[PDB]
Structure formats: structure tokens, C-alpha cells
Length: 112
Image 1 (cartoon, rainbow, N blue to C red):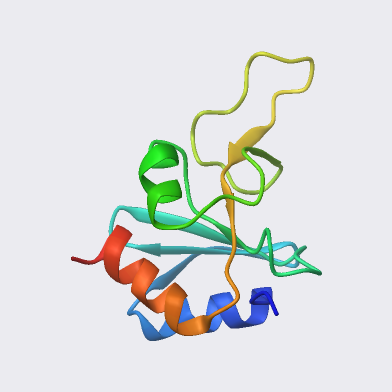
Image 2: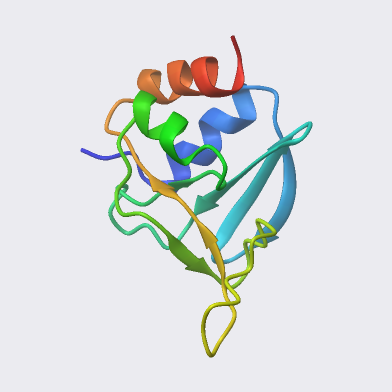
């Protein structure tokens, strides 16, 4: 099945990451200037891996998105959507169904 938020965070730990922001809704994760957010709301591991804007087309070339943009309450990301009544941040929902693929994903997009 798809990788649950538990598993996503676990892989990030192994990859030499650090915690950016911890909440009951998400595990904000960072390694240097690389920021991602483990969507703990992912009852289905399809929207479990939130990364960051900028990498939208690039990231999708390594792994397809589960949506497009997810309006964040906790995950700042920076680009805080001003084009609305309520200004909520937005991250890009990704997801997998192979733990090793997430490893190779971090390998590609954030590693080599």
C-alpha cells in the first residue's frame, strides 16, 4: 500500500535529516536548506510526503503528485497564499508505495 506518515518520517531520520517543526498534524523535516513536511494527516499514505514549492515540475518528474497544492496551517513554506480571503500556506503533496523508492527519491531530488 501507500507509505503511511510513520514510514515517511522514519526514512527521513535515516537519511540524516533533522526536525524543523513538530506538531500532531505533521513532522516538519529539514536537512540543511532542504525543507519537507511529513503530513501526519495522511490516513492514506498518498498525501504523506509534502516537500516544498519551487521543485514542483522537477519533483513531479521523479514522482507524481497526489494533488497539486495543499493549504498549510503549520507548514510555512514561505509562499503564503495571498490570493484568497484566508491566507494559508501551500505545500506540494507527494506519496509512494515503496519505502526504498522514497530512499531513491531523497537520493535523486535531494542527494545526487
